[PDB]
Length: 507
Image 1 (cartoon, rainbow, N blue to C red):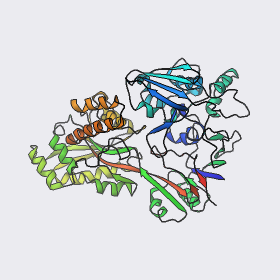
Image 2 (image 1 turned 45 degrees about the vertical axis):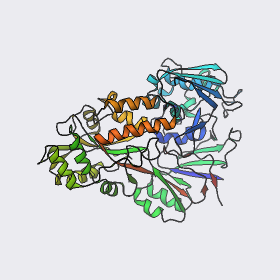
Image 3 (image 1 turned 90 degrees about the horizontal axis):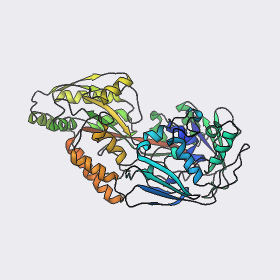
Image 4 (image 1 turned 180 degrees about the horizontal axis):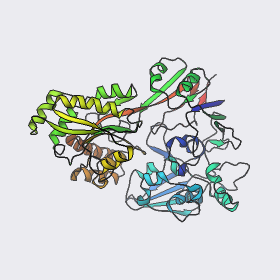
């Protein structure tokens, strides 16, 4: 049994702690490593990983992880472990990142993109060994999403024994280039070009994987990946051309899996601009945003109309959030009501660098421009280079624009706080909107543990946001995993990653 995974580009880094491109994770953390807790398959909730169990103190400040016993690291021709995983390995993995003086902190000229993106420098107070099987993590303030952060790829647990050996041997770089973990697959040290090869770990604590060998074959052309998948020369492909999706849905040889991405494409509105400061005007522009047309024209099937600022996989989703239905007549009337019988002139900043959240900002902008014009809003499309687009948006120069956001941990806090907190102006809160009650709900919700209590708080916060319409959500992208019919037991991951543990091959 050999699964062939055909990927578009060669993975740059085989070390999750120092990876920028989330696609590298599929070649390392996803097969070779484990985390303290792991996301349940297909879900955003966590379950025990290298921690067999954990406790959180009353105040939400202290996380205590009790480590699974008799977990072995892999070996290669350079390294054979003499002890099982313990707290030293966990402390090493966190501290390499958090402690600038740590001996491995600059190994590989490494940059801890995710540690910083998830705000651990400010959230994390300390990571301490209590005993060999107990790790105590203390936060600077309570943060419920932290438990899900711990399950993210960048917090994969490395072997300190291996790291100690390599430092002693004068080649610490090897830690990042020849990965050793506790995970379900072992990185084959003998490697060829245009491919990454793995073998099943017989000693894996969850039980040995069904598939004995994994080949990641670099196959740069989308059309070729598709062709080979039909041919059974690939079992899985990535970055399928959207043009091919419709026919893939008809192909007997293909099992096309799909689900909404944890992202949002929206029209941002600068609520400090004279006309856009007016809530009724914003509601009017919202009524004059043809979301179905946009999704239809722009995503060519690979997207869904957004009703909430996050998809229904996210905690707090509200299936009956009131909508500003597309109605130009109502839009123009609202504009008159707001004191603008002849509308006004404005700008729509077009995003110049395509992202998965929105594969065609230019066409998005054009559709909106045409409808807005019909209600007397004359919006010129404005082009900028990537860096300018971003910097002058953060600084509040824009009026309207085509923007997107992707959540990395999938928690409602990691949509609503970045987008709408006062603290993120100037910053990720492009619209500059704030509301005292809304901000209090976000803080309470981020600092409360109970799931259903959080969900109600988020639903309340989102209703306030919706009433004020500071941005106009229009789409979530759809992620696709095209599989050959032979592969069984693969579960699509909300974050987009591909894990092959638990997967089996027919025929």
